[PDB]
Length: 338
Ligand SMILES: CC(=O)c1cccc(-c2cnc3ccc(NCC4CC4)nn23)c1
Image (tube, rainbow, N blue to C red; front, side, top):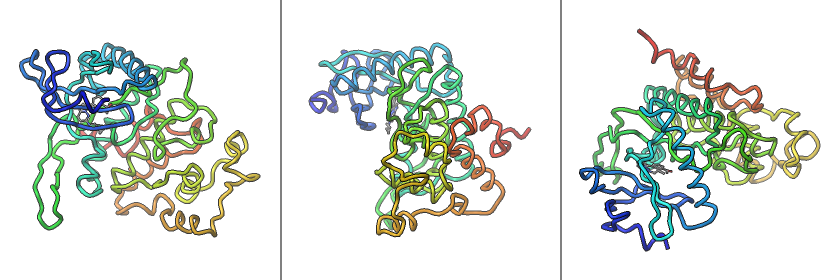
C-alpha cells in the first residue's frame, strides 16, 4: 500500500521527486525529495499510513506545526518548519525543511558509541529550550526520544574504517531540532491513557496517575543518559521489569504513587510484585546499578550533568524539575561564560 507510492523517482503533487528514504516509524515513512518548483531544493516528506489513527494524528500534527511555526517564525526554539501538506493516493504527506541525521541513527551507526560531554551540553540545552517553548504554549510532546531529535545540518565527517567494517561519523556541530508533533497534546485536550515509547515513559504514565508537561522532562532525562552512555539504562519491553529497573537505578518508588495507582497488577501491598531472587530478577540486577555509578568520570562537569539527569528523573511529577529551571542548572553555565 505505502510501498507502492514511496519509490525513488516517484513524483508527488507534481513537484516532489523522491531521491531516498530518511526513515520509518509506526506513522509511516520520511523520504528525501527534490522540489522542482523551489529551484531543486531538497525537502523532507512524511508519508502517513492510510489508517484512521495515523491520519487523525497527522491532522493533529499539522494543527500544532501551524501554531508553533506562526508563534516562532525564525525557529529560535528549534521546532521543525512545515512547508505544506497534500494527499497522494489517499495518504497525507507533510512537507518539511530537510534536516540531517537523527541522534538515534548517529549513535546506532557508530556502534552505540556515546556523544562527547561538550556535544551533550549544547544538545541538552537546545532540547530543553525547544520543549520548554512547547511547555509555554500549553503543549506536552509525549514522544521525545533520540529518533525525534535531528541534527539541523549534516555538520559531521564520515570515514570507512576497515578494522570494524563500518563508517565512523565525527560530529563537528551538534545543533538539533525537535520533530514529530503527531502525539503532542494541549492542556485542555483529552489525554491518551498510554503515551511515550517504553524506554522514555515516565512512572506517572506507567501507573496511569495522569500526565502533563513533566512526563516530557522524564523522557529528556532518559535521552541525556543514552547520549552519555550510547545505550538506555532501561533496556526492557515489560512494564514491571521497567519499574524493577527504576528501583535499582533511581531508588524506591514513592509509596503515594504505589498506593494511588489503579495499576495494582504491578504491586503486592506497599511494594513492587517482583521476585528479585528469580532468573529474570538477577538479570535486571546485573543490568542495573545506582544511577551515579554509570558516570565514566568523577570530573565536576560529569557531576553537573548527573545532578540534572537525577532531577529530571524525580519520580514525583509535582516535584520534578521544570525545563524553565533545568535551563538555569549549573551544567549549562559553561555555555553562558562571557
Ligand atoms: C520523524 C518525523 O516525524 C519527522 C518530522 C518532520 C521532519 C522529519 C525530517 C526532516 N528531515 C529529516 C531527515 C531525516 C529524518 N529522519 C527520521 C528520524 C526517525 C529517524 N527525518 N527528517 C522527520
